[PDB]
Amino acid sequence: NEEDAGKMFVGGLSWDTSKKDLKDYFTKFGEVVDCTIKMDPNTGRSRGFGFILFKDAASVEKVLDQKEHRLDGRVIDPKKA
């Protein structure tokens, strides 16, 4: 594995989605150890994607089993990081 087995990329995030909103959505699939919404270091503006870290890597397969993911009125794109 190139990235941690419990880590996922999450694209298509709405601007009004907070770190807490992100954590609460993925709590449905496993325990979320941590998460982040990536900011542009030059502008401070959101890049519109983030990362989530699960306690148990088994939760990643449960996220990917669900074909469609929706958060704060947007289709979000979870992927193995």
Image: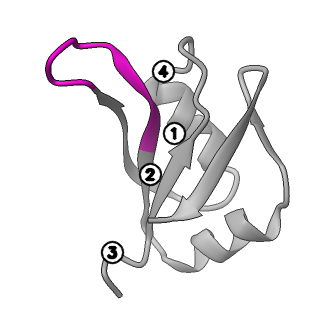
| Residue 13 position within the rendered picture, expressed as x and y whole percent measured from the top left | 58, 29
The mark total stands at 4
**Callout 2 amino acid:** Ile
Between the C-alphas of marks 1 and 2, the distance is 8 Å
Residue at (38% x, 20% y) in the render: 46
Q: Secondary structure at mark 1?
A: helix
Q: Residues within 10 Å of mark 2 (few under 14, many from 20)?
A: many
Instruction: Name the residue that disc number 3 marks.
Output: 4
Range of magenta residues: 40-50
Between the C-alphas of marks 3 and 1, the distance is 18 Å
Between the C-alphas of marks 2 and 4, the distance is 13 Å
Relative height, residue 73 to residue 59 (above, below): above
Q: Secondary structure at mark 4?
A: loop
Residue at (62% x, 54% y) in the render: 78
Image side of residue 44 versus residue 16, left or right: left
**Which callout, 2 or 4, points at the residue further toward the start of the chain?**
4
